[PDB]
Image (cartoon, rainbow, N blue to C red; front, side, top):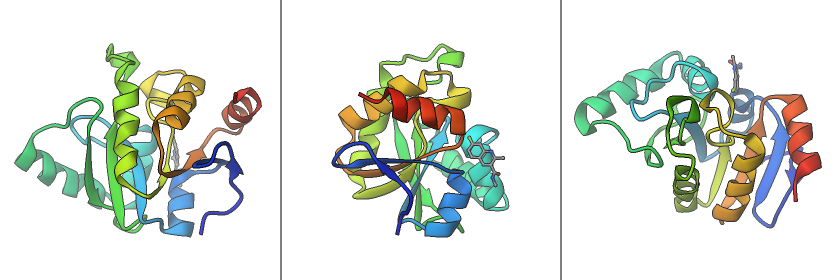
Length: 165
Ligand SMILES: CNC(=O)c1cc2ccc(F)cc2nc1C
């Protein structure tokens, strides 16, 4: 199972790890993708997860979008996890660089509650522009299921653990 995680609360754990490498080692039931409404996995966690699937995640996502249209900001969809997990929960956090509403971050984390255990990144963090300390706070105050957070950046990981209330 998951190893080397620091327990923050009854149900939230955190580790300084590359979510792609973490997904391949563990092969969780669910890996969370930091998706956009179009499921266009270009950069950040999305580009990295997609590149690990040899673009199979993007091909599957384009078929999903052609059939269903785009997701909502704060929404999600369950697709295959390919070589990384049983499933991939594509969650759309607000992108503050695209002027999207930060209040939608709680709605985005609510999607995690439909899954008993997940390997995930901090939503709206990184290239999405939100404050990662705020994202971790929303995560522990919203998610009730078991979440194993993978934080790529070592200096951000230290700042998050050392500042956690
Ligand atoms: C094998 N690793 C990767 O391909 C990789 C992983 C990342 C994970 C999170 C992130 F936000 C960025 C990452 N970037 C990359 C290139």
